[PDB]
Structure formats: structure tokens, C-alpha cells
Image (tube, rainbow over all chains, first blue to last red; front, side):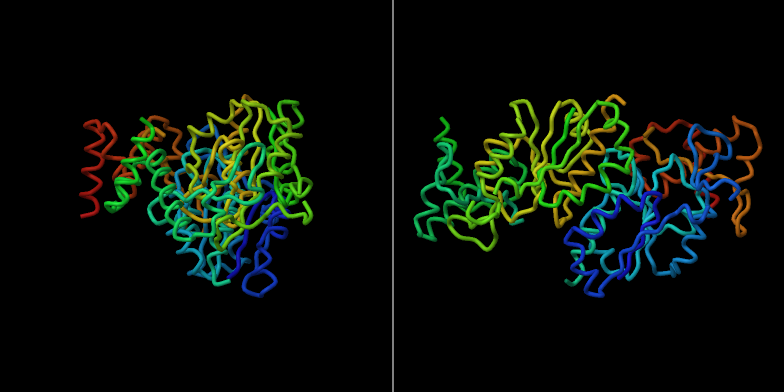
Length: 229
Length: 229
């Protein structure tokens, strides 16, 4: 697979493109992750931005530059063109899975108060948001999504996790549960299972309602609450 | 406000810390956004990582280094310590709002198969996830969240948005709706309102069910569907 980022700030990507566990695939000829400076496709004035027909307070991303960029990037039909949007589908795993299968992805990163509809109908294949929160630009989101998608290339049990501890045993008066140093694995497993139940009960009672509790599980919770008195 | 990132890859941040619309506040003495190299707090071996008591296949982030880092960073009580986690609360706007009010935030960025529970009980104040998708590290998430929080410092109408267009009027046979060039603002507003209704009807019927439709709105939808025949 290969990935292109058409952005006005290709520099934002230097730190991440290299120094992250991203090179696993880059050096392994699995993928080409390269940045594209969008100002190369701009027009009298080298702006990729222009006024809205009908009026409005914001500016709108022009169609021409974007179509041109897609041209030389040889985006075929069956390449994925992603627009970073607030009203886009919030990104998810089923979506990360779907994308890791395409052989080519292009991200329109710049945040504009508007996008020419012709770009949305003819070029863009997926519109994606990160969550109900509002961001200043689409480059971070594009990088975050790349991570999730790439690391899913080739190369819960319904409860919260059991608490984990490492050395030292005692630190500033904070001691690791004795059971963990006992070497008795049936007791360590049982204790972790109890902690998972209890933590879920205290912090994600919704998860408990959708967990098929065994009689022993109910007895653990029952005595736990009696211990709180 | 001030923000610290304790990470093993401070380089990932160079591109973003500067070149994004982040400098608005940095140069304006509103905030200090600086990176901290976590390997400065490491132990015989300069690892921040160590084996799990009780056994397990992954490694666990040691408590000592993290507590030390929080010490010299002068994290007071009433500073926010954030751990990037999969089971953390997915990040949201209400959370972005809450955080933009704190005067100091520290992000533990490294992804480990485990975190010593003492860090979670004594240091960490918020545990946050990005969504059900799994990421390779916590630095991108920390940067994304910073963006949403910072830009919310000081410095929907229930339907999908109306489609936007800019020059040129005709491009590759793709023409901007005539109404937008007509200069008749009551017609432009009505047309946009119709498009919002129609698009929402076709793509987010759930939003239509929670919209207080007027008689005129129902007539727009009604004739639209008759136009589809």
C-alpha cells in the first residue's frame, strides 16, 4: 500500500513519518508514505482557497487544485480519497480494518470552512471525523488514522483489565499485593479475575450488566459489597 | 496554561509544536508547551520498562521513573496527569472543555502493555482513549487532544450542512447550481435549507427523526421523494 497527504504543512509530518514505529513498513517495501505540498497546484494568486458562491462568512476550498493534485497522484478508481471533516463518520476500528485493505489512500488534510461540492461528489470516497470535538486542522487526524490503519496491515473479555505491578515491591509505602509474589498461579489468576470484576463493578457497571456472571462471580461481588459495609 | 509531554520520542513533536496554528498561544505568553525526555529518569539499565509481578507476556511501565518525572515537573495537586489508554474514556468535547480550564497538564505518552497500578492510583488524574480503534503509541493522541483543548482556551442546527461551491462556475462539465449566482438571498437561503433537509433525509435519517419538522419542511421532503419516483 501507498499513502499521500496533500497538505499545506508537510513539515508537521517530518517528526512522525520517521521516528515513530512507522518505518517498520517503509523500509520493508510494503508501503510508500509520502507528503505532497498542495500549494504546487494553485491561479493568479497561489491560493487554494476562494469565496463562496451565494455568500457566506468563510472561504471554500477550490475544486481545480484538488482535481489536479489527484491527477498527477494517479489516483485510480479503487483508490481511497479521504476528507477530514467534523460531520464525517467518526473514525472507528471497522473503518480502520476496511481501509487497511485498499492499495492507495490520499488524505485532503486542510481544514476549510467549506469544500467545493464537486470535490465531494467526484473525488472524495470517505468523509471522516475524529469525534464530536473540534480540531484546528486535519493533519494530526490523518496521521493518527494512518497509524491505526498501517499497524493493521500484515506486518476485551467484557471486563476492565486486571491491575498490573512491576518492581520494586514497596515504593514510598505503596506495596504490590502479596499474592503476585507468591508464585501460586491459580491464586494469581483468581485474584486478577476478582479485581477485574470489582473494578468493572465500581467503574463500568454497564459492562457488568452485559457480562454472563457465573455463581462464583456473583459471590465475589456479593462479598465485596459486604466488605464495604 | 502549560503542557508537558513525557515521551521517549520528543522528536515526533517538533513538526507539530511549531508549524501548526499552535504558536498563536506560545508566542503570546498564554502557555508553555514543552517536551520532556522520559529516559532522563531511568536504574542499572536505562529502561523505564520492567517485568510484571505474577507473570504475563508484556512489560510494565515502572513506577519510580514516572514519580520522579512528576516531581521535578512540579506537578501540584490540581495539575492534570493524563494517561493514553485503550480502555480510557474516549476523548470528547465535554472533556476538551473541562481540560482547557486546568492550568497545567502532563501527558504520559508511551504505550506499554501495562502501567504500574501505583502510577494510576497516585499520579494519573484522567485516563483517555481516542476510540475503539487501537494505536501504536500515545504521542499522536496527546497532540490531537492538545489541539482541541488549546484552541478552546481564550485566544449543528440538527441537520447536515448545505453544500458549498466556489469558482469556477463550470468545471469539467460540473456546474454550480444557478441559484447561487442569482443574487436573490431569500432564494439562496431557501435552497440551502432544502439541500440540508434532503441530504439529512438521504444520509442521516436519524437526525430527521430528532428534528422539529415544520409543515414546509415536510412538503419539501414529500416532493423530493415524489421527484425520485
